[PDB]
Image: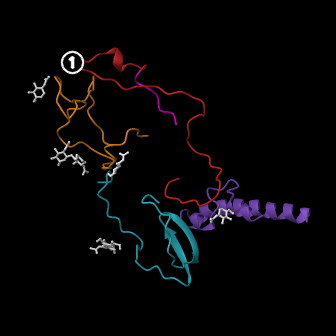
Amino acid sequence: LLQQLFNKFGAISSSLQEILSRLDPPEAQVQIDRLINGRLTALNAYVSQQ
Amino acid sequence: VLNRVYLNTTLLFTGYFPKSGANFRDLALKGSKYLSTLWYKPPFLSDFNN
Amino acid sequence: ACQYTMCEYPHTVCKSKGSIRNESWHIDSSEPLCLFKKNFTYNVSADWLY
Amino acid sequence: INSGTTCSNDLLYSNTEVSTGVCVNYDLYGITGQGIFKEVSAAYYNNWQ
Ligand SMILES: *[C@@H]1O[C@H](CO)[C@@H](O[C@@H]2O[C@H](CO)[C@@H](O)[C@H](O)[C@H]2NC(C)=O)[C@H](O)[C@H]1NC(C)=O
Ligand SMILES: *[C@@H]1O[C@H](CO)[C@@H](O[C@@H]2O[C@H](CO)[C@@H](O)[C@H](O)[C@H]2NC(C)=O)[C@H](O)[C@H]1NC(C)=O
Ligand SMILES: *[C@@H]1O[C@H](CO)[C@@H](O)[C@H](O)[C@H]1NC(C)=O
Ligand SMILES: *[C@@H]1O[C@H](CO)[C@@H](O)[C@H](O)[C@H]1NC(C)=O
Ligand SMILES: *[C@@H]1O[C@H](CO)[C@@H](O)[C@H](O)[C@H]1NC(C)=O
């Protein structure tokens, strides 16, 4: 579960700071939405397994 | 790896390596007095993909 | 790494005892445009280099 | 202009301010993050690393 925070999931980076430093606030939300969806999916799968 | 240090472990790394079990290609040439033309052809002018 | 005026039949000359021909892989004595320039060192007595 | 190497760097802050003990933001040679630094003696860095 800790290694899920190093997947890109379709975004250009796995880092929330390399997106906010290198993209405009319109263009950053498209990548932050993909990271949010990938990490929420990982948490749902873990919660069902428990 | 570029400027990274790894210590007492194994690493699974995707990179740019030779294929294990492939052969080489001697392209060195030693002239003495003359300068050919068939030396300068797509036999010796080669490709660069990766 | 520069844009050079490349010869048709390029070749070199050993800088220990000179040969019949001259080292001429370009004729560009006007300092052309360059992307990169550097100098590195290696062991003079080592046999194999990769 | 606008093609070559003689650049007017204008770098953020290559400050000699490695402050140990507290949380900082870092941009170390391209890698970004946050963390607490703590000085040590280490004998495994070659000159390319
Ligand atoms: C890299 O090294 C080469 C060879 O040591 C340098 O070329 C010499 O440059 C000086 C000054 O321009 C000339 O007087 C010599 O005749 C050159 N030697 C040869 C063999 O060409 C070169 O300048 C160095 N490059 C850098 C960026 O320092
Ligand atoms: C302007 O450029 C100078 C170039 O000298 C910068 O000062 C250098 O900073 C580095 C980083 O520690 C040192 O290694 C150099 O020794 C410094 N130069 C000197 C002459 O001491 C400076 O930081 C730059 N400032 C701005 C505002 O761009
Ligand atoms: C070798 O690597 C293992 C990896 O877990 C580590 O536990 C061990 O301490 C290492 N050996 C030394 C001498 O540091
Ligand atoms: C090599 O260059 C020198 C000086 O320009 C010249 O005298 C000599 O004839 C050249 N060699 C050949 C084979 O042309
Ligand atoms: C490498 O260089 C060192 C010093 O420059 C020398 O002592 C050593 O013999 C060299 N080894 C080879 C294989 O060239």
Crowding around mark 1 (Cα neighbors within 10 Å: few <14, some 14 to 19, many 20+) is few
Rendering coords of residue B32 (x, y %):
23, 20
Question: Which residue does the image show at 71% across and 59% down from the upper left?
Answer: A34
Rendering coords of residue C19 (x, y %):
18, 25
Instruction: Indicate the chain coloured orange by its letter.
Output: C
Q: Eyeballing the image, is A31 above or below C24?
A: below
Secondary structure of the magenta portion, mostly?
A: loop
Q: Which residues are magenta?
A: B44-50
Name the quadrant containing residue C22: top left
Instruction: Indicate the chain coloured cyan by its letter.
Output: D
Q: Colour of chain B?
A: red
Question: Which residue does the image show at 44% across and 26% down from the upper left?
Answer: B46
Q: Is residue D5 magenta?
A: no
Q: Secondary structure at mark 1?
A: loop
Q: Colour of chain A?
A: purple
Query: In the rendered image, which residue does mark 1 sit on?
Result: B33
- Specify the amino acid type for callout 1: Lys
Q: How many marks?
A: 1
Q: Eyeballing the image, is D16 above or below B3?
A: below
Rendering coords of residue A7 (x, y %):
69, 57
Q: Eyeballing the image, is B37 above or below C39?
A: above
Nearer the observer, D29 or C45:
C45
Rendering coords of residue A18 (x, y %):
57, 64
